[PDB]
Amino acid sequence: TEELDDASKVINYYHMSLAVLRHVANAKDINAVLGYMEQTGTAELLDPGDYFNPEVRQNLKQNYAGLFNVRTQFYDNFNKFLAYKKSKDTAKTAQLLDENYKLSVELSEYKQVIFDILSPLTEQAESELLADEPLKDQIMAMRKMSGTVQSIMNLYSRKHAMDGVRIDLKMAELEKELKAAEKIPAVTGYDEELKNFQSFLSTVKSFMNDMQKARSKGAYSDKEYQAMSEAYEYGLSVI
């Protein structure tokens, strides 16, 4: 079938995006650089094909261009900062840190816009490829919650600019998805899969308790981010 191949090209595009974005726009790498600056003493593989409509292709291209542009500015400013720090130029180093704070948020937003574009498309493709799967509803629910968790972590990961209000909106979205998932009817002959689905739900509630606490501090913490990224990496995996 033509639609099945198109649906698998949407999934593969998402996987490639997730791999590239995890390598070039990783919050831990960006926040480590910002941390250093505070111390007082080829991407043509992502060209989207016609399995996406023209608006979607243009949105992806513009957001990836923006992402790489703000990433280059960020690391250029960091290398300029290292030269200025040696030159004892306190005025210029402060300006570059101020610029790199704004650029780190822009980089995070571009990454979020790319995931926002792909999320309903990957969802539609998965619904087609899993049409004959007895646990379609369970798989779909976990995939969507994993995406919502990843969006919350992205919003939290913004060192010097933790976005509380957007975290809260995404937590309400996650709570709504969780209550719907808890109502998914069990399928006979899949008790092993059901136990691991129930463990997924329990891990989401744990994540939510940890994120409520982290978010209540009103600011990004390297300690909270490292703890939560380690605790939920494998359990709430967005692959």
Image (cartoon, rainbow, N blue to C red):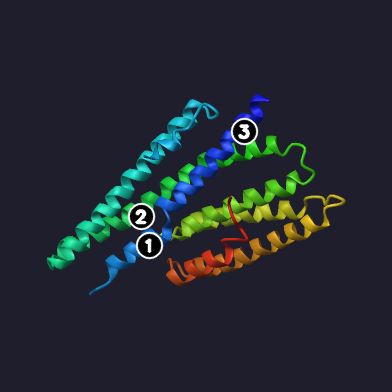
Q: Mark 2 sits on what residue?
A: 104
Is 65 placed left or right of 184 in the picture?
A: left
Comes first in the chain, label 1 or label 2? 1
**How far from the left and from the top, in percent, is residue 79?**
23, 57
The N terminus is located in which quarter?
top right
Dot 1 lies on which element? Answer: helix
CB-based contact (under 8 Å), mark 1 and mark 2: yes
Q: Name the residue under label 1.
A: 31
Q: What residue is shown at x 46% (from left), y 43% (from top)?
A: 113
The residue positioned farthest toward the bottom in the image shown: 41
Spatial CA span between label 3 and label 1 = 35 Å
Q: Callout 3 environment at 10 Å: few (<14), some (14 to 19), or many (20+)?
A: many
**Between residues 224 and 18, which one lies in front from this camera angle?**
18
Q: Residue 171 carries which label?
A: none
Q: Position of residue 154 (x, y in %)?
A: 48, 55
Number of numbered callouts drawn:
3
What is the secondary structure assignment of the residue under circle 3? Answer: helix
Q: Can residue 191 be seen in this view?
A: yes
Between circles 2 and 3, the one closer to the viewer is 3
- At a point 36% along the width and 64% down the height, the residue shown is 32
Q: How far apart are marks 1 and 2 (CA)?
A: 8 Å
The residue wearing badge 3 is 7
